[PDB]
Length: 221
Length: 213
Image (cartoon, rainbow over all chains, first blue to last red):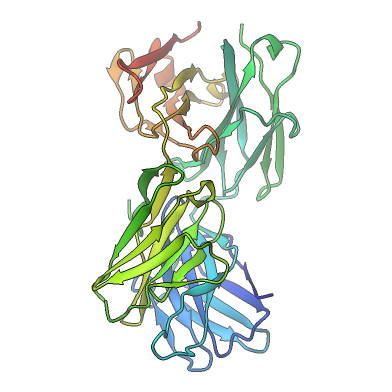
């Protein structure tokens, strides 16, 4: 079974460098075409590069020409994408895709057949900051939640009641504040009668910084 | 600011509908147009390749056709698993380009949002910043306007929105607007309001509060 595995992404500073690797299985990448496609958060797909080790030809999108170099190593059946002079707009999920060899000169391009799961690359001068979790005060059914704020980089997984409360939860997509840090909210809708007896604690998980926070929510006086 | 790709356009449809997404391709001789399907958090999946050929494993409701320069993707009977984002791909001048993106969305009756406004937690005021959030729970369509009012003064530029993905069964959306203020500016005003307008609201709904109950 053909599989494409991306790796190498993470946090990089503006003007810094990064090198992604696309380890392939199930097929020999030699005669085929390896591509790199990136997708900004909430945006569409953008092809950036294509490589064919048989012909050695490298083709890049105009938005990355001169900064991105695509290559491969047939010894390990792995392609590479070296990114130099990285800018903030280069922050995206980077997929590596495979295009089959030109077997028919009429149907010369038969689409990007298989894709990888993609690796996230964040270009920002911010530092890895732990999330600051704050409770959302709950004033026929009441609404409460948690506000996690000033964390970097993405993502953050939020659970409720150690993963036992799932019906009615709303973990919103994160927003990028002007300070370069991320901030999202996670609300929930639980009956007001069970607000005093049943305790509601949100489990905030930031794996980049290894910060586990369990903040309880209670109505103010 | 510097957007590298436009956001995916929306298309409201019901299950069983017949949809046809057109891809304007000036490179008609490059009839290698391919269509892809992408769902939230997942990688794109090849559906149509070489303008009209069906990829191995894709249901029969998907079809591709080319009429001169216009390439189309047609779903005969829209199914619950078909609501996703669809991209068109063109190969031209040694460059591969993807389309803008068409997000097929489930259509339902209009549902007014439930509004809740939450003052900041005192642990945050001690940090030096105030964050008032406004919750818009379970509404349709996703088009909603949130206006922050500080002492009956209309705000702009000191808030950020965030809308969730459509619910699979309710077909609803949820918005969270976070008004961020400093500890000094927050203590200088009393009433903070969150005005919400929607298609299902004949009049704007305001959920407000006073600093300190």
